[PDB]
Amino acid sequence: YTLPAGADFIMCYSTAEGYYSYRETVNGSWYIQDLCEMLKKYGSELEFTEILTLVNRKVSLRSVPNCKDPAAIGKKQMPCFASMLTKKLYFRPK
Amino acid sequence: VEID
Amino acid sequence: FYKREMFDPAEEYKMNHKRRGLALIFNQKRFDWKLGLKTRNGTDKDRDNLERRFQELGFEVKAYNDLSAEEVLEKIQEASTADHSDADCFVCVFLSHGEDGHVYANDAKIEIQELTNLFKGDKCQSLVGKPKIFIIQACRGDKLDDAVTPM
Image (tube, rainbow over all chains, first blue to last red; front, side, top):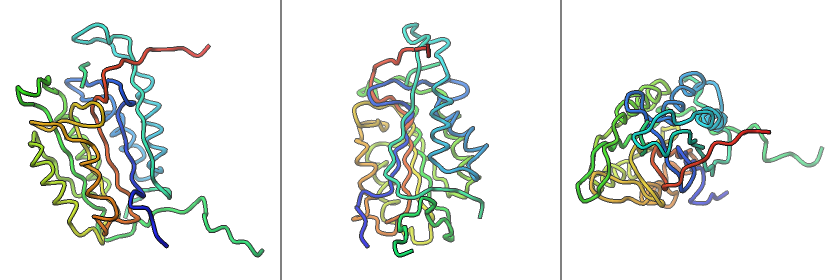
């Protein structure tokens, strides 16, 4: 029984590689806003990658409403997690 | 919204 | 039946240790003139929000604001060489700008592999086989994604 040294990492990125991320100056960034909202609702109930997939869905439906430079208005953001996990991860209460 |  | 399934799809990480573990938060708001990066206003709301949910889940949260790169690695190494024997796992969050495969500290680039290497099994043994969670709120480039509609 040996594991790779690289085993059981999970890289949760707010946006896909090469792409912008977006941030509200009062409420904070889209991704952390939605990540914490999903964690508040299901942190202790759901598998971590199902949460990240919910976060994926939530950020995906947003649209840049207004931007200090208008070329990002109407643009989107798709987050992306890279899983090297080997089991289901839960934070059920203890 | 800002870019970061 | 002679062949037992050894990879059960229901297998879960054992999350019954004494502690939940460390969550580190690296909140980067302001940067050196030499970096030429704009100030990430709103990130403290991100930090306060993460610290709350991570505390609700049992983690010990350590939030650092505007550290230098050497100081980030110092706190990373401190986490890397700690005793995680009775921790369920480990979380590390990074709130900054970035591109390529690096994020920015207060003064300098940091490749994300610098954040992760100190936790690879060959260096942080008390976490081997435990989940290591990294969250990056950062640009990863300068493309914009267009809006499309299902037909």
